[PDB]
Image (cartoon, rainbow, N blue to C red; front, side, top):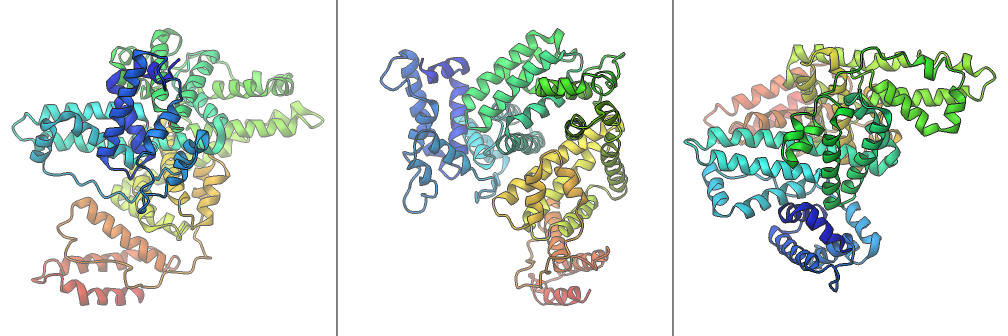
Length: 579
């Protein structure tokens, strides 16, 4: 009784008010901060009413009803804040669904440039709780699918970094460091959770259960199948609740799962010892990031149970899901060197071969050669990674980003230029993150993280579809997304982009830029001129790009006031369309 009191008691008031603030920020991303704080105060005082007496006049309602009622106190400002008045006009489940379906992955929110370190330490120590609520509210409204318990862990490290380095000699050499690494890990955190929610919402929980079986058997190889199955069921419920807006239930169940894992370490893995001593948030984060355990040495081959046995078709028919779940578990525990998407491709190939061979006349002869169908599927990513990494170690991260940017702009010239720039930069970053790994586990690092970056290209393009190839590659099937995009070639059906009045913008504000903003500006110009000529652009885009670099260096080192950028910009647009 009184579900809201049950959540308040299990989570504690501090984690309660933080998770509710994250939920409000993720549902109304354009609502101001103070309105969210007022409604958070209201429902937590109401939750105190309910744990005081679980028979009070409104404590039996559902969390969605309570949060949706409090959210629609402000959510239909008829001026123009009425685009989500859709849901406030609905009720029951329809309104929550409407709320979920209105989450914006690329909102029009302004760039959060935050002030000098002294102003931050001042606003921090003036009121720590409002400073940290502001951090939560901003990250949650700009990342509406952010893993909520992980966000609590990020906020905890955020406040610890501020308490530490605001009482130092130089507040810059201590704070901005950890702030930037927190920001990088935050965007990696939310992109990974974005893939999880997209897989759940667009492919059902069967796809996530299979993905979880593969990943958990990779990491917990000494665990028995029933143990992995139990962990997979609980992990799928945690991420299902959380991707669907049930953040309090997401967090409470995640804590219960961390408690169960750390109570049964001896039947799961040998590498949970030091993570299982940490506090709640640190414990769950460490469990979710632990390295793969040592696999059992004398593991039998799998042909005896899945290829050579005469009960293959009978086991595939009487208990289909258990049989192939056991197959994926037995194949994933033996191959930590394979990526998860590859292991799911092999599992689906095994299932399809079993489908067509169990209907034939000599099934054993038919499915005895199923392990050969896996050779091309294993060879393709290994080649892709070795060639792209030996190209990366030649070019370096920045030029590797430019190479992937030209490649994918040739593949899908219709996709928005900013999204193209961001996805290719995040595509290039997998070279620095994984190519440096030993090839021992070079594939799971790269392809799985590629599945993350490409998923962002899906959800950013999903909201404004313009390329049918992106739509096909992202909707046909999850585990095949990387080959679909990899096998694409130049779009010969795309009519190029003529030089337009604002194809690019060059004022004096390009020299005073940081090193990343200037890379993004040049990469944006590179996207635009590849869109101007997708073919016949061998790699003499180098010629136009070096001419462009000579242009901005010249008109910057001049006595001008970007007057040079004006009529030497008309000279650039002339000399570039000729090439």
